[PDB]
Length: 170
Length: 164
Ligand SMILES: CCn1c(-c2cc(N3CCN(C4CC4)CC3)cnc2[C@H](C)OC)c2c3cc(ccc31)-c1csc(n1)C[C@H](NC(=O)[C@H]1[C@@H]3COC[C@@H]31)C(=O)N1CCC[C@H](N1)C(=O)OCC(C)(C)C2
Ligand SMILES: Nc1nc2c(ncn2[C@@H]2O[C@H](COP(=O)(O)OP(=O)(O)NP(=O)(O)O)[C@@H](O)[C@H]2O)c(=O)[nH]1
Ligand SMILES: [Mg+2]
Image 1 (tube, each protein chain N blue to C red):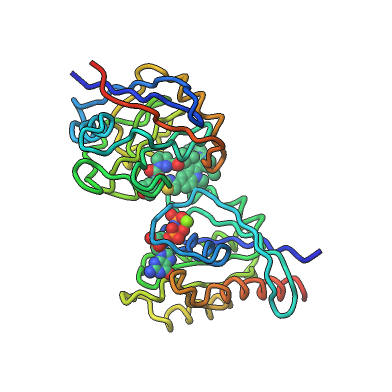
Image 2 (tube, rainbow over the protein chains, first blue to last red):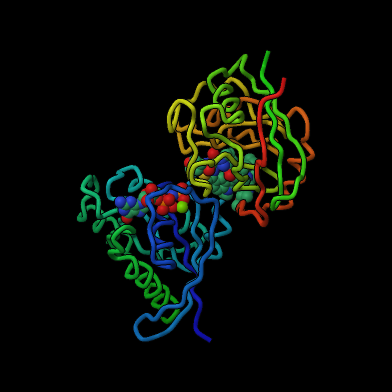
């Protein structure tokens, strides 16, 4: 059967992890805020001509539970590291998630995509070059997204699968 | 003279039982008054008919979204949100009644009932009451919950009000 990819969506509270995931899976967006405990989703997709199954863990950004991420970082194969382009603190919070992931994997080479979400909003505080530089420094792709307009949503998840493939095909 | 309110709980429309609460108006009068008035429905809206949308065994039962019925809404009698009144009272054990929120100063109508001590919520959620009678009804609600809180039957406040 098709290969399954275990994707994990991480980032600060409110950056749009769930809105991105629900847009990908269910093709809709609501502006209501439903902070996540933990949710899992499945979707089959075609990426670079090859059909596969995305198993997506949508994690809590709720900051008080940072000590409870080890198990899902051990199980996950690739990580969507999400910040919001109008929230500089959420961009600063990226580093700590990547540090946690690198420690669990004991590796600098973990499949990961940096996602700058909410690019539909006019209130930007993180410029594209700043995020591109960080992604380059991490050695990972950077994609700007909007869960509201769907800009970049498929691309961000598909790019993460391409990163997992590159890591598990060498 | 702390007020007392009750919920008559139903499970997919079938009566389960009554839970009653003491509201600590002596320590958190604004927060207690909100919950009291929402329990009577005296503003023309309130808890009657709403559900417990998140039940996590070992931790708490959460409800109070009577505006959207999807866990994102609710409103207080003061406006959609009101400030954290104080954090005098702590989450000391089962039965504690405390305000849900989405960050500082975002109290509305959502609330939770502890089924264990939840001390890591101290200083972030306003404690304002406790179960007085019917704690075993709250305990019976836990088997309709799950790890992430999704419920397997509709747990509703079939009736509610204020006791003498
Ligand atoms: C990391 C997993 N995880 C846990 C958790 C944690 C633990 N521990 C922590 C403590 N350790 C001890 C020190 C050793 C033991 C292990 C174990 N297992 C779990 C769960 C079962 O693993 C899946 C939690 C938890 C809580 C959240 C997110 C993830 C969480 C979370 C998201 S949003 C919120 N919290 C506040 C929320 N806000 C809204 O709903 C806003 C909605 C919109 O605006 C109005 C309305 C709100 O007010 N409440 C009212 C208060 C209880 C609270 N919900 C809630 O549900 O807590 C759930 C839970 C289980 C108590 C905590
Ligand atoms: N304009 C706009 N709003 C967005 C976008 N993505 C999310 N939002 C809004 O931002 C809020 C938070 O989104 P949500 O997906 O719940 O964020 P989260 O990262 O899953 N939060 P948590 O960690 O608490 O689960 C919601 O009001 C949602 O509608 C986006 O791309 N554009
Ligand atoms: Mg979420």
